[PDB]
Amino acid sequence: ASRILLNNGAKMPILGLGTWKSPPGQVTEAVKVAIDVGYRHIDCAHVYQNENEVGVAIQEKLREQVVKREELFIVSKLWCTYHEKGLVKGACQKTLSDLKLDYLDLYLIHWPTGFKPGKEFFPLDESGNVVPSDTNILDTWAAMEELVDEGLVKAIGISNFNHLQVEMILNKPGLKYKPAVNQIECHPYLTQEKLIQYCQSKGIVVTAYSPLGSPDRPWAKPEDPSLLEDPRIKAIAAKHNKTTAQVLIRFPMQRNLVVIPKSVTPERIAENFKVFDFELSSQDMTTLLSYNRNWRVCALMSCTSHKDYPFHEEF
Ligand SMILES: NC(=O)c1ccc[n+]([C@@H]2O[C@H](COP(=O)([O-])OP(=O)(O)OC[C@H]3O[C@@H](n4cnc5c(N)ncnc54)[C@H](OP(=O)(O)O)[C@@H]3O)[C@@H](O)[C@H]2O)c1
Ligand SMILES: COc1ccc2c(C(=S)N(C)CC(=O)O)cccc2c1C(F)(F)F
C-alpha cells in the first residue's frame, strides 16, 4: 500500500527521500536515482541550502519523461526566520523557484519556534540563546492557509509540534484548513505513542524523520545509542533476511506513518525502497516499540530557551 489519504483529499507516498545534510554536489544525482528506482516523495527545506540542486533533478526527470508532475509529491518547510505573516509567501516563492515547481504538494511550518527575521537562519545573542520572534503560530497558520487559497501549495502542515501545539492549531479561532501532516522525529528509541495516537485521532498523518537515527548528524556523540548497530534490531532484520535499515523503514510504515530516510548513496537509496515485500509480525512491532528511551537526534538544547520550544513535554 504505497500512499495514504490526507485530509485535503490528496494521496501521499508513505516512503520519501530525505535531503537534510545531502551535499549540494551529490543531491542532484541522489534524487535522480531515487526517482529512477521508485520514489515519488522528496522531503525538502529552504534551510538545507540544497533546494536548487534538488530542483535540477526533479526538472530533468520531468523533462526526460521519467515521471509526471502529478505523480510526484514534493514537500518543503517554512524556516523559523520567516514566521511573520508578511514573509511567508516570499519564503514559499523562493522554495518554488529553487525546486523549479509551480506548486508544492505539502508545505510545513518547520518548527513551532519563530526566530528573529533577517539574513541569519540561526540568530543568537551575545551569549548564544536563539533570538525568538514575536510571531504567534496561529498567525503563521493563517498565512499558510492563504498559500493554499493562492494555489501555491496543495496541503499545509506542521513539524515538531507537540500535543498542546497541535491542539492550539486545531482550536484556532476561524480555522480554515486543518493541518494535513505533523512531521516529527520517530524511531524505536523515540516511539512517540501518545503524540502519534493524538494526531491520527484527529485525521492528521504523521511523518517520521530520522528513522535510521541520523548517523550523519553533526553533533553525534560516542555514548549515543545506535539504531543501526543495535544487536536486537539486527536480529529482527536477520530473521526476515533484510537489512537493519529496511527494518527501521518498515517499522513506521506498519504504524500507518510516512517515513523519509535520507541517503546520497545510490545503493542505499535503492535498498531503502525495497521495503514493500515483507512484513514485521505483531510481536516484532511490539518488541521494536519496547526499545523506547526518549532519545532525540534533534534535542536542540540552544532552543530550550524559546517559549514554543516543543520538547519540555514528552509529547
Ligand atoms: N522537520 C524536521 O525538523 C526534520 C529534522 C531532521 C530530519 N528531517 C527529515 O528527515 C530526513 C531523514 O532524517 P536524517 O537525515 O536526520 O537521518 P536518517 O534518514 O535517519 O539517516 C541518514 C543517515 O543514514 C545513512 N543511511 C541511509 N541509508 C542507509 C542504509 N541503508 N544503511 C546504512 N546507513 C544508511 C545516510 O548515509 P548516506 O547518505 O551517506 O548514505 C545518513 O548518514 C532528513 O534528511 C530530513 O529530510 C526533518
Ligand atoms: C528550532 O531550532 C533549531 C531547528 C533546527 C536546527 C537544525 C536543523 S536545520 N535540523 C535539525 C534539521 C531540520 O530542522 O530539519 C540544525 C541546527 C540547529 C537547529 C535549531 C537550533 F535552534 F538548535 F538552532
Image (cartoon, rainbow, N blue to C red):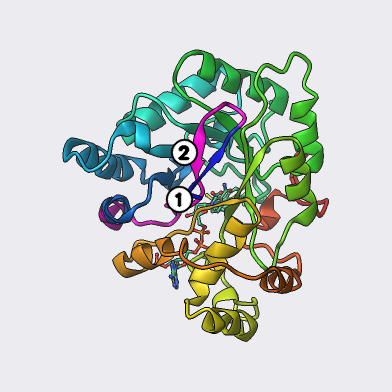
Q: Position of residue 49 (x, y in %)?
A: 39, 45
Front residue of this view, candidates 117 and 264:
264
Q: How many marks do you count on the picture?
A: 2
302 w.r.t. 205: above or below:
below
In three-dimensional space, the C-alpha distance between marks 1 and 2, rounded to whole angstroms, equals: 9 Å
- Say which amino acid is labelled 2: Val
The picture places residue 273, in percent across and down from the top left corner, at 41, 61
> Do we see residue 215 in this rendering?
no
Q: Quadrant of residue 65?
A: top left
**Residue at 47%, 34% in the rendered image:** 119
Residue under label 1: 16
User: Any atom of ligand 1 within 8 Å of the CB at mark 2?
Assistant: no
Q: Which residue is mark 2?
A: 75
Is residue 61 rendered to the left or right of residue 311?
left
Q: Is residue 271 above or below residue 152?
A: below
Residue drawn at x 61%, y 51% is 257
Looking at the image, the residue that sits furthest to the left is: 64
Q: Which residues are magenta?
A: 7-29
- The image position of residue 307, as x and y in percent, is 78, 39
Q: Tell me the quarter of the picture where residue 172 sits.
A: top right
Q: Is residue 12 magenta?
A: yes
Whether the magenta-drawn stretch holds residue 34 is answered as: no
Asked whether mark 1 lies closer than 8 Å to ligand 1, one says: yes
